[PDB]
Image (cartoon, rainbow, N blue to C red; front, side, top):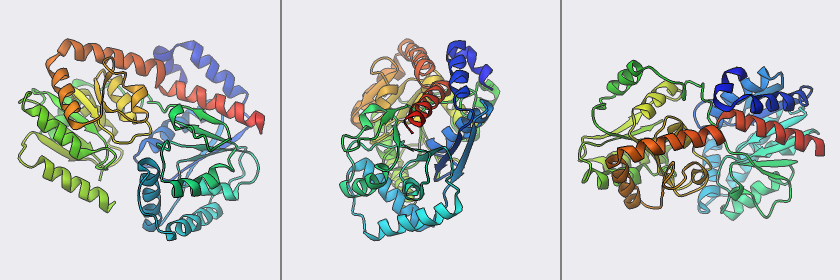
Length: 396
C-alpha cells in the first residue's frame, strides 16, 4: 500500500504520485514482456502493476508465448545488442516476425497506452491501432550488432516514445522522445523486506554456508554477461589474503548457460569455500537472506542495463564491487557506495580492501542505503513512469 512508503520517501512524493494518477484515471494501459518468472523486468512488473491498480489506473500486464526456437532467436538478439558481436542467420528474422503475428492475434492491443518491454515483443508495433506506444528498453543498446539493431530500429521508429534505464543508452539514430528512467526496488517486497535473524540463519545454514566467516555473494544467472568465471577468479586471488572468506554464487538454472555453470564448477575446482547455488525462480526470501548474511556483494557484470541486485545489496547496507558498465555506474559511486572494477584483479584488490576495513564497509553500507532511498525506490520509478505517460499521451 502507497501509505506504507511515506516512512521511506515522505508525503511530498506520495501526494505528487496521486496528483499524476488523477490525470490518468481514464486511460487504459497494457504492459507486454516475454516472462512472468525471474529476471529484472518480471520482478518490476510484479510490484509496479499492482501499485498502478491501487492508484485506480486501468493497467493490464500480458506475457508473450514462443517456441524454444523463438527464445534462441531473442537470446541471440539480446547478446548481439549488448556485445556488438555474433553471427545471426536470416532465418532468425523470419522466426521473430512469425511469433509477433501469433502473439498479435492472441493479445488485444486496443489500449490508450501500450508499454512493450525489451526486444522480444517489439515487433507487436506492426499490429498497433492508435493510442500511445512506448518501447521500454532494459538492456545496453549503446554499441549494438548493427544488423540486429537495424532490424529492431525498424520497429522502434514506429513507437511514440522510448524509455531507457540511463541516458547513456539514448540513441542518436532515433528522433522519437528518449526518456531515462532507472529501475527501482520495492522496499516492502519479499526480496527486500526486513527478516528476523532466525530466518537468515536458517536459510544460510540450509546451504552449508558458515555464518561465522565472511561471505562474498553474487546474485545473478550463470550467463557470460554476469561473468561467473571472473567472479571465481576474483575470489581465488582474494582468498590468498582473506583465508576465512567464503564465496556464494546464487544463480537460477539455455545450453550456453549449462556450459557457463560447467566452466564455473571447473574454475572453482580445488576450493571447498566456493558455493555455486542453483535456486528455483521466485526464491525471493532466500535471495533476501543471503544478501543480509553477506559481508560484501559483487555484481561483476561485463554488460548490464541496470542490475537490480546492486540496489538490493546497497539497500541492505552492503558495499558492492560492480562491473564498470551500464547502469551499475549510477548505483555504485566509486569509494562511496562501492567500487567499479574493469578486471578480476581489481575486483580482488577491493574485496581484500573491504574485508579488512570494517568501519569503511559499514560506512559505505549506510551511504549505499541512503543512495537507494533517494534514487532507486519503486515510488521514484512510479512517479517518473506516470510523468512519462502524461507527457507522451498529451503529444498523442
